[PDB]
Length: 98
Ligand SMILES: [Zn+2]
Ligand SMILES: [Zn+2]
Ligand SMILES: [Zn+2]
Image 1 (cartoon, rainbow, N blue to C red):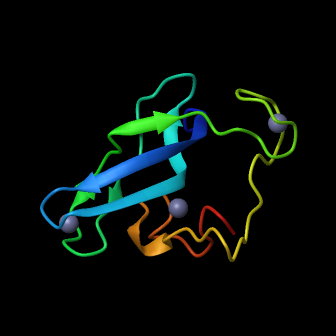
Image 2 (image 1 turned 180 degrees about the vertical axis):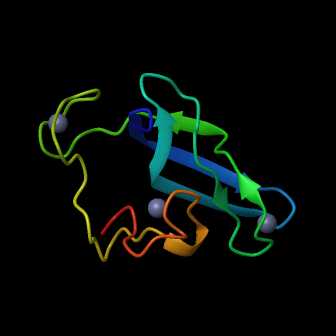
C-alpha cells in the first residue's frame, strides 16, 4: 500500500509568473506538513510545493484532524480542482475531486 496521505489546504505562489493559487487537495504525508505531490503553475508548467499548508476545517463536523470520510464536497462547481495541474491525478481518468 502507498502510505496514507492527508488532504490539506495549500497556498501557492509562482514568483516567475507572479501567479498565486490555492488548493483544497494538497496531499501531505499523514500527520505532517510534508507535501507528497506537486502542483503545476498554469502558465510556466513548472512544479511547486505550497509555501503554507493548513488543516482543512471539515464541513461535515467543523473540526480539524477529524475522522469523517469527506471533509469538503467533491464534484464542486464552485471549488474546481485543476486535474491537469495536479501531481496526484493529472495522469489518471478520475480526478482527486471526482
Ligand atoms: Zn509559473
Ligand atoms: Zn469531520
Ligand atoms: Zn488531483
